[PDB]
Length: 38
Length: 54
Length: 112
Image (tube, rainbow over all chains, first blue to last red; front, side):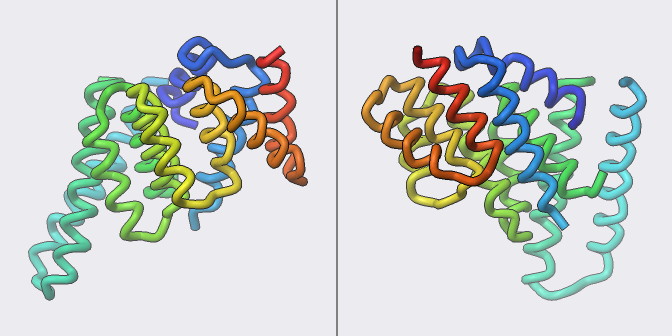
């Protein structure tokens, strides 16, 4: 993922007050959605 | 990486210049609706990259 | 990068950095090209980053995407809709997708 997007993902924990497990699963689903583009 | 920024900015700028050249070819109104959408998306992306990564 | 993937990632950067109209212009293009799930992800991210969880939730529950379910659960969590969140977690726990299972496990822990 673009570095600036990863920088935003690295702030999800404090922005939404969620733990690392939640963030990792969401980052993976996000990556998965982008991987479906032809 | 500064290099990835430079690279993706060049990719978007080249795509925008090519699209503006394609828009000189003429076409029907539906073709211009497609090209206008793409053009605005590219301009928008270049803007975000400038504002955020500089 | 495939161009549309690059544009989608940039739109997401836009939604997390207060450039919502720029991100929407990109989504209008992605919509024309049929990447409706990415369009919905950009819309949810834009609304949620602005703190508009209610609008996010209303829009999310009107367009069905299995992989985006966690975002709607996050909206319920941030709005403090306890009952809705619990209901959503029970439904998501039924998914065969290991990523969804990881999310549910993480949210249950978060809630303890």
